[PDB]
Length: 51
Length: 53
Image (cartoon, rainbow over all chains, first blue to last red; front, side, top):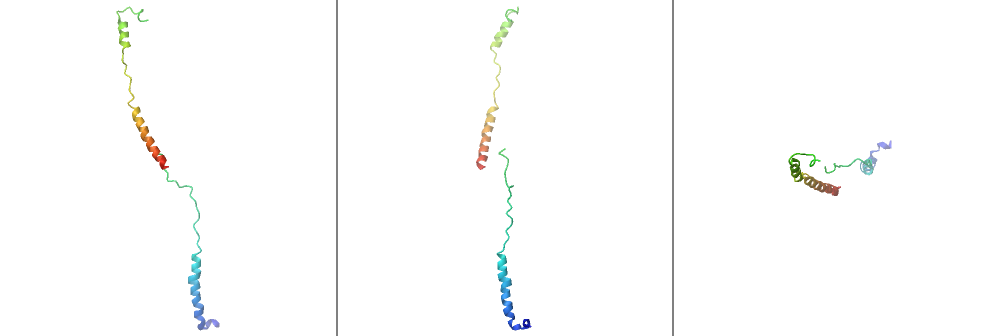
């Protein structure tokens, strides 16, 4: 089994740690879901006329 | 009706004299000036609030 040849094990481990812990995560951080544009038509800090 | 129908000595006549020259007290306002002042104050407050609006 070529999977047991431990000589090429760093070549398979070092890029993965860059791809899984740096690049894919930097691409998920740039995937953002903004909160809904919910517009409140009820917002009026008013008060009775000056009486 | 009270000169020619009253046979009494001048009582009608002195009554009419005392009545022709009676000073009946005309009441004074004493209350409109202060409500005018209150209207001025209220107009001031209302114009201030309107500038805010």
